[PDB]
Amino acid sequence: RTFSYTLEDHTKQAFGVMNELRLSQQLCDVTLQVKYEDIPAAQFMAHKVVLASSSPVFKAMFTNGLREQGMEVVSIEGIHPKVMERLIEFAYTASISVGEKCVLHVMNGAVMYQIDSVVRACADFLVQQL
Amino acid sequence: RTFSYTLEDHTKQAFGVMNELRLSQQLCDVTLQVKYEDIPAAQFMAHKVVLASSSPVFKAMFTNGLREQGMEVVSIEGIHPKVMERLIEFAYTASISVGEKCVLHVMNGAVMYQIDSVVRACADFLVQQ
Ligand SMILES: [Ca+2]
């Protein structure tokens, strides 16, 4: 005989704790430094695994080579802090919420990190405004 | 107007990748060394955030002390490797599967790491037997 059990809510509970840890700045091993014209650089701390889990681009970036130990700082250009903030929040929560006139720029930021699900959703939202 | 989107399956997909990373032994920042009487220590590579997300014991263990630089090796005693394996698998997949006659020792491990859900399921199983 075999005992089996699965907790249906597990991955949502778990992500809830991981997001708490991100906001507390605990266990974080990467800092995203986001530089946008004529405004100060912003910093977002996160966990590489979590970014990897949602984005093949971050996955490739953090499994390639092997970086000298500790806090990695990654320079990001071409994307507003607030777009990156929203992609990060998506990785950690499963949700994103954006002013309708800026959906195009979020989409492009999701393109850049190959977050296909938010690329599609953005796209479908733009197509129903035609 | 506002644009709103949630991907309902996101957290299952993302745990699927995190689990692949664990099995490919990439990005790992902790190696558990599990020692058990008259058997050599077994190693298990995992991601601290992930273990912390599923176990307050792991959470406390990795948030206490200093922001560790790189791979930490951690001695563990009082749990067979295979019990730890199944708890780690549970953390990363939401599922655990064990032969009936060892449910008790799995329950004990889940108590040790304060995985409450698997404690309750193991209890439930042992009472209706
Ligand atoms: Ca408890």
Image (cartoon, coloured by chain):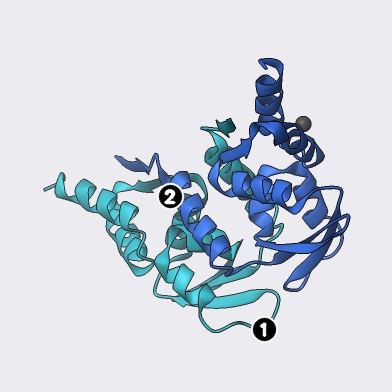
Chain colours: A cyan, B blue
Say which residue label 2 marks: B13
Farthest residue, direction left: A130
Q: Say which residue appears at 84% left-offset and 65% top-offset.
A: B66
Position of B9 with respect to B60 (left or right) is left
As rendered, which of A29 and B79 lies closer to the eye?
B79
Which amino acid does the dot numbered 2 rest on?
Gln
Query: Residue B48 location in percent, x, y?
Result: 69, 58
User: How many neighbours does mark 2 have within 10 angstroms: few (below 14), some (14-19), or many (20 or more)?
Assistant: some
The x, y position of residue A66, in whole percent, is: 59, 82
Quarter-wise, where is residue B111 in the image? top right
* Residue type highlighted by circle 1: Glu
Q: Are marks 2 and 1 on the same chain?
A: no
Chain to which the residue tagged by mark 2 belongs = B
Label 2: element kind? helix
Secondary structure category for the residue under label 1: loop
Q: Is residue B66 left or right of residue B115?
A: right
Q: Position of residue A90 (x, y in %)?
A: 45, 51
Contact, CB < 8 Å: mark 2 with mark 1? no
Which residue bears the numbered disc 1?
A68
The answer to whether residue B53 is seen in the rendering is no
Q: Is residue A55 left or right of residue B103?
A: left
